[PDB]
Image (tube, rainbow, N blue to C red):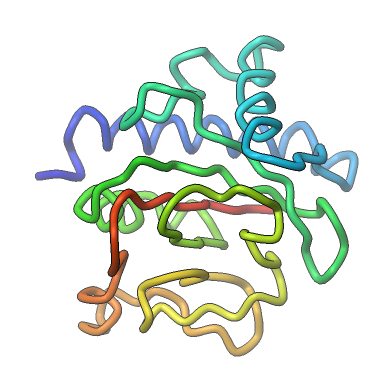
Length: 174
């Protein structure tokens, strides 16, 4: 199956390693490192590698061969209280497979067309209401009233990652 492909297996392992490193490092500080743009996000990812908090292979997006980006964003209006690992360059098929294969490790999921260029593009970890029925934008979050991705809902399954490739999925935690 696609979920067991070399790249999908690596993307699951990498996302896990990176999110664990992020929470282990900053859940003690209360705040995540500010990342103004895509460049700052890919520098943060490379920083985890240089400091030995994850291997070089673990920070890589297996679909692009470059570093996944790590954006710090707001939670309940408070700046940098959450972070999101961005996996871009995804075809629609890779987006559907990746989201459903690693989605359960993340409370926040935002599917976008194109890369996240600014913190504003991510929304808010706690106040952005999910609507998986649209298969786009925030499709999973802790927000009262959010309609999170549910695989038993055929609408959620068909609409997932609808649109134009490449897609970038932001997997967030706090």
